[PDB]
Image (tube, rainbow, N blue to C red; front, side, top):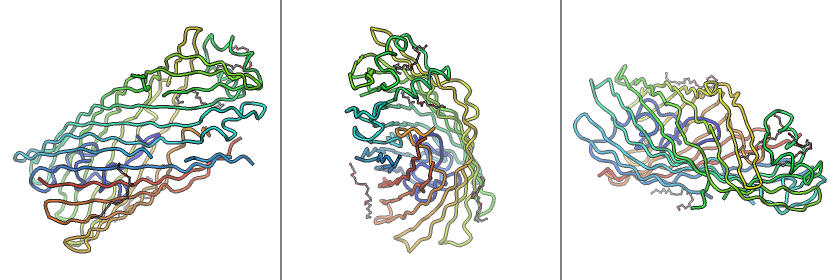
Amino acid sequence: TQVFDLEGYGAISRAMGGTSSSYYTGNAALISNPATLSFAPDGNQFELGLDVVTTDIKVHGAEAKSSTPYVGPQLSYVAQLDDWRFGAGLFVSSGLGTEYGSKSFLSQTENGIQTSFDNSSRLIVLRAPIGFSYQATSKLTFGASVDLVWTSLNLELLLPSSQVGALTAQGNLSGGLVPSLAGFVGTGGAAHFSLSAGGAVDAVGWGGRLGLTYKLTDNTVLGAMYNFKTSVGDLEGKATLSAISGDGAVLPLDGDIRVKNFEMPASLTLGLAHQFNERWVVAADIKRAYWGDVMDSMNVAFISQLGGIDVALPHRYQDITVASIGTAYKYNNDLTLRAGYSYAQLILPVIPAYLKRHVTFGGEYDFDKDSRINLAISFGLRERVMLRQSHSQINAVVSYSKNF
Ligand SMILES: CCCCCCCCOCCOCCOCCOCCO
Ligand SMILES: CCCCCCCCOCCOCCOCCOCCO
Ligand SMILES: CCCCCCCCOCCOCCOCCOCCO
Ligand SMILES: CCCCCCCCOCCOCCOCCOCCO
């Protein structure tokens, strides 16, 4: 998910700054760099995880806070069969999460009138890969995976007269419902979208992933994996447009939205992992999320009986280059403590921008040598993005790999 595109997935990878390319990082490697999967301890792994995110947004004097938690699964298994590793897992996760609720100015119709409309968002994505890793020459490990993605979303966005007009001017907002709803909303209104068998407003695309590894030294590994842009489908499902008059009179139309071109771009990451001491470990990858390679427009069509409304949004997103280092010491044949960091390189309270800086802590507590527990937590370092607004996330994951 991450509401634009970044790096770092997995219980042990999150802890190491989202490094992943060259080394082992559990079954998440299925959605990271399947080649890496080869390094797995002989046998058949079987992890269970609990990924967790939460954002604290503070938009503005006019305070509007975010919180007023979605926890996702991680059933995965990676069987072995000489030189050949085979895995398949489900990987649920949030990333987009806000709940300003109905009380703040985001709920203030033009003319600062308090509507009782909610302002919230939640994008959930469940990746589900099926791939493999292969040992070709105790130096070359190839691996790839093809996953079924299932995106779901629910919004509670409110737009004041102003920006609805702004959307018109820009040549973004077309419709038919517009003419007619104009003059009822007027320079003092606000429109409001609400998505909640009930469609749910979800989609079902496909994802691709292939990567390699090369033991350059016996203390240096080189890695790379290409990530095909996921082919999500169209987000479809019941929704409710509510023209709100310049004084609070609500006109609710019920129809069905269709979000088109929700892009999750491709990415090529390159990294290494050195171990200049049979205890202390270090990792480092450079990621490239190819956003500039997205030229079409995200289209939000809404259809009711009385008519429709549509918003076009062209992409215009340049490339994102993520650099990230990792590390991991072994307190002993029990504890393993890791810690990494990763620097990455339209105020809209309901969809906060990805953060660039990140600090990550974590460790691993083995207790069987056939069972293990990984624990990671990543800090989204605060950025200050008229409407001043700022936020900072806290991601925490925990997986228990019962080496069968
Ligand atoms: C965008 C998420 C998909 C959910 C559909 C809701 C569609 C509603 O409109 C989103 C448009 O937001 C843009 C802001 O308002 C325009 C302000 O003027 C800015 C000029 O760049
Ligand atoms: C997105 C919600 C739809 C509700 C539309 C009400 C917003 C309309 O505009 C208010 C600004 O007034 C000026 C617009 O021009 C008059 C009619 O609209 C025609 C545009 O093709
Ligand atoms: C050779 C042994 C490993 C020693 C540490 C490796 C550290 C290597 O470099 C990592 C570079 O990436 C992180 C830098 O901070 C981000 C700066 O902006 C750069 C553009 O991507
Ligand atoms: C034997 C080692 C002990 C390590 C335990 C790690 C588990 C401890 O907590 C980590 C932080 O908790 C994360 C999320 O909050 C709990 C929510 O409920 C989740 C399942 O529905």
